[PDB]
Amino acid sequence: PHELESQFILRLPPEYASTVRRAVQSGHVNLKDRLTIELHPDGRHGIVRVDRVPLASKLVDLPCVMESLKTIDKKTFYKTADICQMLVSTEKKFIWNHGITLPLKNVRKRRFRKTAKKDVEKEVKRLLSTDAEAVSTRWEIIAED
Amino acid sequence: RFSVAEHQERYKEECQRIFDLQNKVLSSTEVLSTDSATGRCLKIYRTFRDEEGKEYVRCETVRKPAVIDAYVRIRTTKDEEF
Amino acid sequence: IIQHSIPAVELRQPFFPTHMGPIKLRQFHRPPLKKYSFGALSQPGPHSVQPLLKHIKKKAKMREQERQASGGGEMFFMRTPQDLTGKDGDLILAEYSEENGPLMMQVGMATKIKNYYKRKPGKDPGAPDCKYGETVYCHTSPFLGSLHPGQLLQAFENNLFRAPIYLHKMPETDFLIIRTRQGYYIRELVDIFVVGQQCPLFEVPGPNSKRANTHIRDFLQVFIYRLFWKSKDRPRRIRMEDIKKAFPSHSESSIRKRLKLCADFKRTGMDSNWWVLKSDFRLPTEEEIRAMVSPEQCCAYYSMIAAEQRLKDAGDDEVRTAPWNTTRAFIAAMKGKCLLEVTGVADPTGCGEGFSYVKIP
């Protein structure tokens, strides 16, 4: 059938970013050779080569949901894909507490509400599995001291 | 003690003030600098048979409230089912 | 007024999910980066990004030529999923201030930017020119707060909701990368819109609501009709297992009740183990199938199940924050049936900024 395209933002050093932006504007095949993206099996890390120079990169999760919109006439906009991940080239480090826009900054601790992580439920399932493995399970309560 | 006119006026002014504030904060290009009720923990004792002949007993303590609440709810539901 | 893409109106399964798993419900409009089972990306190693600047200009030129063939009249080019892909055309980014929107557009849905300008008292120079959207003039602001005279605010306008948008320049460090099984692709992005709190123009159904139950039945029936169209056999026939794979949550008996009308089952002879279409029954036309289920209805249902999953995960204030209550409250405020307290637990920001959609006397 059809597989939805997956889009992730890429963040690069400003000197490196300026060279890449000029190459993108040129549209030359040299840009394809200059920039290569490698994805780790874990997928929480990436290796990016800029101008054939390897840079350590870690994937981070954008707090806000960002949608790419394409409009032929500039009056009608059609959503193409949803971006929730950014790869940065130079857990709480796998999370980004800051929005891409300058206004939205420290969103997690400002323009966001306290939300449940679910994770915790999976940990409870592991405890239930250990109870099943154990021949006998005993429950007791300890008061805070 | 106007109940409708006073209430409507306050609702309209508060909404407009919030709308102006929300627009200003989002439109701003200014950079921003980076910045249980019981109080009782849960302890579980598990008895298992090891390889050959052994009956080791393991005591595990959970100090995380969310995990404790989820575990207790499942245990109570299991008791309710039987 | 808004026209959705042909895949979005057809409610195609990749664009609109038949069923969502509990982990998928938690990841609502936030897909994880998947690892392809097969393909060039699947093999481990560095992968070169491909410049498609020539492709973007060529596709735009081809669309312009098609418009010239139509006489220069505006033409709808999004007739296929391949057209929907973001690699070609002009791409803009919208970032939502709310962590979770009450209503979120599914992929392939369309929105029109509307720039609302209030004229300055007496003589006015005019509305500011806007690159995106069409400028309009309203005596009364659509948003609860009245627009100041001489002020123009761009907004996203769609059947589901209307949200104010603010244009901001994209960071030079930021770049957009579109990853496909064949290869990575890179597109520069220059414009991003901050999104103000959404004002719902549509109502999310409550869990176990009569409307929610009707939508679930309609979606299953529409999928069954599409399966009959998909079958190339002269006596159209569908497998019960295929519907079950699409809807694991649905009971076999509920699927059987939809199948009982308009379909019959043979256990022996030709078409054995197949649900053949009734000869007397006439299969509904594509326009009728689109009429039965709205894309807006699907988005509201998808929002409700994701919110219900979040409520279930988090063990009365949270119930008020839930979207179905907020959507009903906002519609009541537009009717004028009841006022909404501006400050409430339902506020998405959790701060004075933003509005809380909670019914108040």
Image (cartoon, rainbow, N blue to C red):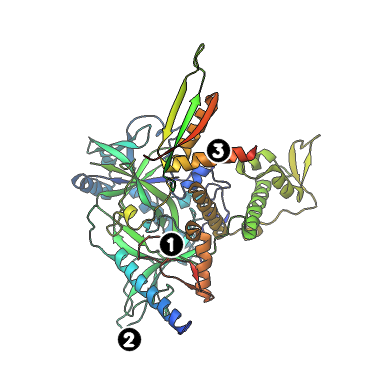
Which labelled disc corresponds to residue C345?
1
Q: Is residue C65 above or below residue C136?
A: above
Q: For this rendering, which residue is in front, C317 or C17?
A: C317
- The local crowd at label 2, few if under 14, some if 14 to 19, many if 20 or more residues have their Cα within 10 Å, is few
Q: For this rendering, which residue is in front, C312 or C165?
A: C312
- The local crowd at label 3, few if under 14, some if 14 to 19, many if 20 or more residues have their Cα within 10 Å, is few
Viewer-side label of 2, 1: 1
Of labels 2 and 1, earlier in sequence is 2
The answer for how far apart the CA atoms under marks 2 and 1 are is 38 Å
Q: Which residue is the site of mark 3?
A: B75
The answer for how far apart the CA atoms under marks 3 and 1 are is 32 Å
Q: Quadrant of residue A94?
A: top left
Q: Position of residue C19 (x, y in %)?
A: 57, 46
Q: Which residue is the site of mark 2?
A: C121
Q: Quadrant of residue C168?
A: bottom left
What chain does badge 3 belong to?
B
Viewer-side label of 2, 3: 3
Label 2, secondary structure: give it: loop
Viewer-side label of 3, 1: 3
Q: For this rendering, which residue is in front, C195 or C62?
A: C195
Q: Residue at x 51, y 40 (%)?
A: B72
Q: Residue at x 42, y 76 (%)?
A: B11
What chain does badge 1 belong to?
C
Give the residue type that dot 2 points to. Answer: Pro
- The residue furthest top is B52
Q: Position of residue C136 (x, y in %)?
A: 40, 75
Give the residue type that dot 1 points to. Answer: Val
Q: Is residue B32 above or below residue C129?
A: above
- The residue furthest bottom is C122
